[PDB]
Structure formats: structure tokens, C-alpha cells
Image (cartoon, rainbow, N blue to C red):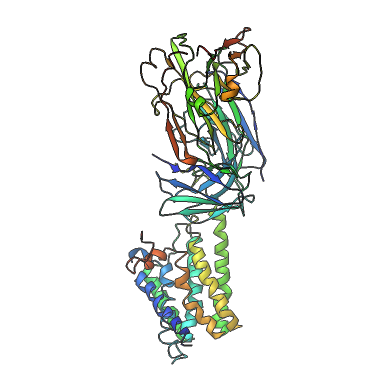
Amino acid sequence: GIVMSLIVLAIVFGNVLVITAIAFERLQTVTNYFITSLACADLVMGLAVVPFGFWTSIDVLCVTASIETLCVIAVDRYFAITSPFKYQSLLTKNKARVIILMVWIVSGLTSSIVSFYVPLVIMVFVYSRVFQEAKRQLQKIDKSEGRFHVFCLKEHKALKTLGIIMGTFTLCWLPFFILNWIGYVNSGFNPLIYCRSPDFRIAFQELLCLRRSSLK
Amino acid sequence: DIKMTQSPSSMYASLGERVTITCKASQDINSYLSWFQQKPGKSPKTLIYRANRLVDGVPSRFIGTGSGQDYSLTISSLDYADMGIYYCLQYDEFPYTFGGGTKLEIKRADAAPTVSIFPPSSEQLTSGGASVVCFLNNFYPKDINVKWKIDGSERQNGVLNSWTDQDSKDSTYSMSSTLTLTKDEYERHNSYTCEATHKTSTSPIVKSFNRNEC
Amino acid sequence: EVQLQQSGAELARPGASVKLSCKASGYIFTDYYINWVRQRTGQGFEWIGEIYPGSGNIDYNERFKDKATLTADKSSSTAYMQLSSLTSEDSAVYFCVRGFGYWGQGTTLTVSSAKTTPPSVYPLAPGSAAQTNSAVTLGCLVKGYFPEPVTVTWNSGSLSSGVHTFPAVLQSDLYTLSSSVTVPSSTWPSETVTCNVAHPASSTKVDKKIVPRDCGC
């Protein structure tokens, strides 16, 4: 209770250090545009849902937009790999927003098979396909490349970070759709896996006037 | 995991000629093989990878050419500095596995050793004992031989021997034999000879010394 | 100016655990993985594993699977290897390569119960003023030290042409070795000649000039 109170500032901090992190130049991309989406679907669901807990209205519009966005990226990232060119989906910056805007109202005009099954039924395979056909390439590479020099293993971990974010939101909201507090847990797990996995590490940990390893 | 034989093992080429070692793996590494050289007293210097792609800096007389399951490092016009142990490595799959490396020596012209023997430096003597050193130097063939003689007598008890690999310039062989003794051990004898017997001659090369006038 | 620095000499008691480092400096650490290959005395190379500094992937070799654990340092631009529960057979030279391209220096790790003991450079000068050559060959035997290795230069690196140094042979749980040298008789007793020696395992450097002789011998 009064002990778990420290769990809200967690859904009001980590999700803001992120929104601001995105809102730096280099951090602005389609991927970090949808991950920055699950920020308002964790902060709003913490400064508007967690506090008072219309209250059951934004409780659905929040969780039905998550496993929906998770369905988005899983496909976006795919279209990025299946693509004949470089790794970075074609969803333009504006059409990412226009596509972003339509994920909320449809999340508002919205069921476990509509707002949960459907979005997780495909999202797990559109990604499965990906995490898989991302391996064939991973080393269809030149072995010599990297040891004699004179998509790579890096972007292979970027799908590891996006590979657990989609892999934690499943074991957190499944036992519920099959415990209502376990689902809230994925509110301080994303900005937590982004530290020891993706670039965010420095992006936001050093934004707080150089955290620690700032050549301390 | 993936055995990779490598003939030859031992090998003697004279300057100018083209020598060649051949490496044949168990699997089928897609030309994902490399060739390097281990020189005594140094870290291995890599010459080729991707079965033929010379590393940057490696002299243009080195040549790697195989494919699929059998390759071969080769050099035309063998240069004197080209003495050592070349090994082939495959990085096609885990675990990376090395060949056994063949070793190449250069046949030189027969040359006897310049032998020299030193008595125990006063310094050590004072310390507590005495070791005597004889140096059988710059000689070819590699097969050399020594026997210590003391007061006419003769013995091989407690002698520490060691030979070197083929020298760079002289492309010759040199050996060091020491008969570690004691201040006392040493003090009980007057004459001390070092007899080297090398193909070069039939008469042992010899060097002696007495512990008195000295 | 490309290089991966290494310790060169590492002593450890049986059952303990050493942690070799390798400070690469001359390229972009995270652009090449770096493997660690062990090469025991005598001859032979056995890959211990490969860690890609840039990502994190550390593919170990089954054998050293649980024995060693690779690790990199993006900042320091140096990498490491954790070797636990060392044994008499874990002793050998450990190489830190940059993917088989450029090799490291080496770290003469030795797992032993033995106590370190530095050398004893003694100088060997010609016996009885035997002016029997256009040249001369003196030397300096370094006796009893441990563990290996021992750098042995002459004239502080200055002299090179005609200097031999023989491989440390053991003898009663203690290393002994020696380096001889030839120069023009027209030079030595005339111009100074020293023999340097180094025993890292004890951080011991030593110089030893060669005074002609007792004038009597």
C-alpha cells in the first residue's frame, strides 16, 4: 500500500525521462516513436488511472492501445527487414503520426479477441518471422568482416530490446486475459530494459546532469 | 569439432626456391581459412585470410590458394628472413580450430662452431657457487655435440643445455652448455675443457682452462 | 601504432583465479571482435573464445565454457578474460587477438605453488687474455629465477648484430638462461658493453656491465 506508493512515481518518471529523451535529434525515429507512444500509455495510466486507483474508460484505451502498438512495430520492423534496402521501416515521420493518431481513437472506439487475441495472435508471428529471418542474414555476412576488415549483430540486439518489451507485456497481461496488479508492473519495466540493452542508457541516464559512469 | 591436418610438418628449403605447405580441413570452410607465422620469441604475424587475401604489409611473395576443403600457403623465391612455423586457421564455424602448423628451416652451407668457455665470475663464486659456460656458436648442420672434461677425466652430470632456432642473419645454429657446480664442487678440480664435435670436422673443437694461474 | 597491450607474466596459486587484460589502442575497439587463444609451451594453439566488444556476443569454446568468461570495456577500450580454479595445466601463454588479424603481446600465465625469485645476472668474460680473433664473444648468464619470462637485451637494446640468447631451461624448480655476444675485439674492452635483463613476474630490471677480467686470468 503506502509502500507501493513508490511504484507510481516510477510510472511518472521513467516514462517522462523517455518522452523528453525523444521529444534528442538522434533519438527521433519510427521505432522510438512507437516506444515513445507506450510512454503516454503508462504515464497517463499512472497519473490518471493509478492515482484514482471515466476511470475505467482510460483504463481500456490505455491497455488496448499497447498490445495494438506492439502489433504495429512487430510489423513495422518487419517491413523494415523484409525491405530490399537499409534497416528502418518506410513508415514516414508524418504517416507514423497519422498512423499513431489512428491507434488511439480505434483504441477508444474499443473484446479479448478484438483488443487482445487478434493483436497478439499475429504480433507474435510477424515478429517470430522477423527474429528468425534476421538470423539467416545475421551471418550470411562475411565471416572475415569484423576480424580482418582492413544489418549486423548490433541491429540484432535492437530487436533484443524490442524482443523483450514484447516478451514482457505478454507474461504480464496474459494470466489476466486468460493478477490485475501484475499487468501494472509493465509500467516500470520498459524504461528499465532500455538501460542495459539499447542506446537510451546514456540518452536519458546522463541527461540528469551526468549520472554516474560519466567518467566519474 | 573440425580436424584440420597440415602437411608438411618439418621442412628445409634453401634461399630463392619456392616452398609450399598445404592445409586440408575436415569440413568445408568457405575459404574461411587464414595463414600465420610463429617466430621464436615473438607473437604470431598473420599473412593471409579468406584463403588468399594477403594481409596489409605482408610481402607479395606469399601466396595462399585453396578452396572448399584443401588449401595451401606458398612463397616463390624464399627469402632468408622466411624461417619459422606457419599455421593455418579456420573460422568458418565454432569452435575455431588451428592446424598444427608446419615448420620451415633454410639449408645453409656447412659451418663449424666458434666455441668459447668462461670460468665462474668472481661475483657468483663469492655468492655461493660456480657455474661454467661454454658457447658452441654459429654452426650448420644443426646436429652438434659437447662433452665436458675435467682434469683429464670426463662427465655429464648436472649440465644444462639449450640450443637456439635458426638465427636470422647467419641462418646458422648456436648452442649453450653449462655445468652448474658449487664453490666447493668447482674448487676440487684444476683443468676444465669443453669439447665440441661437429660434422664440420673430425677433430673435436676444444677449449680448456685451469683454475690456478686464473 | 596498432596494439593490444598485455601483462606478459602472470603467476597464480593452484585453485585460484587470474584475470588477464588486453588494452588495445590503435583502432576502434568496437569494429573487430577479439578472441583469446591459449598456446601452451611447446607448440599448439587452442581457441578459448571470442567476444565482440561492440555488441556483447561471447561465443565460448565448450572446453573453456565454464572455465573462462570473456568481457569487454567500451570506455577503457581494453578487454578481459576470467580464468577460474586454475590448475597446473592451465599454465601457458594466453593470446589476445583482434580476430586473428593482429595478435597481442602475450601473458605468460603460470599456475604454481612456487614462490617468485628474481634472476642473478652474472657476466662471462674471456678467460686468459686469449686474443685469438678479429672478434670477441662475451655473455651474461641469468641464473635462477621464476616464473617465466625474462627479457634480455644487450647495450640497452643498442647492440643487435651477433647476439644470441638461449631459451630458459629449468633446473631444480628454478629457471636459468644465458645470452652470449660477439663484437670486434677492436671494440669491447675499449668501449663499454652492458647486458640488460628483465623479470616482470617480479618487476625486476637489471643491468650488468662487463669488466674485462681479473687481469690475471
Query: Which quarter of the rendering shows the N terminus of chain C?
Result: top left
Q: Residue B62: percent from the left, percent from the top?
A: 51, 28
Could one spot residue A78 in this view of the protein? Answer: no
Residue at the bottom extreme of this rendering: A54
Above or below, A69 relative to C207: below
Disc count in the image? Answer: 0
Q: Residue A178: percent from the left, percent from the top?
A: 61, 83
* A32 to the left or right of B138: left
Pick the front one: C200 or A158: C200
Q: Nearer the viewer, residue A163 or C104?
A: C104
Residue depicted at x 57% and y 15%: B140
> Residue visible at 49% across and 49% down?
C33
Classify residue C197 by image quadrant. top left
On screen, B102 above or below A216? above
Question: At 57% across and 20% down in the image, what residue appears?
Answer: B187
Is A140 situated above or below C133?
below
- In the rendered image, residue C43, in percent from the top left (x then y), is placed at 61, 35
Residue C82's x, y, as percent?
54, 52
Residue B86: tell me if it is visible.
Answer: yes
Q: Nearer the viewer, residue C89 or B64?
A: C89
Q: Is residue B42 left or right of residue B99?
A: left
Q: Is residue A192 left or right of residue C41?
A: left
A126 or B116, nearer to the observer: B116
Left or right relative to A110: residue A212 = left
